Length: 165
Length: 164
Image (cartoon, rainbow over all chains, first blue to last red):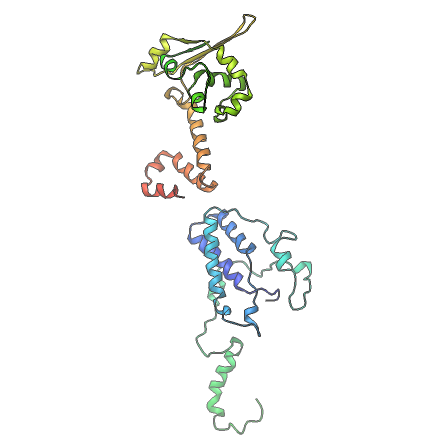
C-alpha cells in the first residue's frame, strides 16, 4: 500500500511456492521460482481507488494466483533463478520498488528498505484468519454493528428520545 | 608404411583426388595423414576448405604404401578376436624411422570396454546437451547410469523424460 503496489504480489509469491511444491520442485527450482515472482512486474493498485476504481479489484488476485502457476511451471522446466533479486543495488526489488513512499515520493530511511518480520513461518495465519460470516460490513465495524443489534430492543421505542450515543 | 587388413584395402584404400567429404570419409590414407599432422581427427577435417588449406595431406598421401598383413586379415575374421588392425610406420629421408605403432582393436571394441565406456558416456552427455537443457540432461544421464533403476523403469516413463 505505502509504496503504491497492490497486495496481490503476495498471492503471486505464495502461489508460486505452494504450486512449485505440489509439482515436485526441489530447493533450487523453488528458489528460482520465488525469485521470478519477485523480479516479475507488480501491479499498481490504481483500480482500488476513486476516481479510477473498477472491476479489476475483483480479479487481480485470480490473475496473480494464475501467474504463480505459470512461474512454478517455468521453474520446473529448469529456468535459472535470480539470487539477489531483492537486494541487488540499483536493479533489485528493494531499491527500485520498496524504497520510496508514494503519498509524498519520500525516500525511506536505509534501515526500512527491506522486509522485516516479527516471527517465522508456521501455521499461525490459517489459525487466525477472519471469515465474513455475519453482517455485510467493514471488519472494523463488525463488533459495533453486533452491539447495536443487541441494543436495538432496548432503544427500539425510545428512538426519538435519544440525545447522545 | 601402413600395414592393414584385407577389408580396409578393399573398401577405403583410395589413391588420387578426393572430390567431397564422403571420399575423404572413406579414404584410409586421408584418415591416416591428417592425424599424423594435426594429432587429431574431427569432422572439420573432411572439409574441402581444410583440405586445400594444407597441401601436406596429399604429399603424405602420395608417400603412403599400403601393405596387407595376412594375420590382420585372418584375425579380422576369427570369432575369438574380430580384430580391425592397422600398423603405421614413418620413415625419414635420412633413412631413420619411428617404430611401427600397431593398434589391433579400436576403442569401441569389446577388448577395450574399460577405456571405451568413459568415452561412450561423454559422447552421450554431449549429444543429450544438443537437445535438452542441463537439469533434464542430468535426470536422463543419472537414470541411464544405474542398471537396476533403469531396468525397473516403466517404458512410458522413460519416454516421458525424452519428450520435447
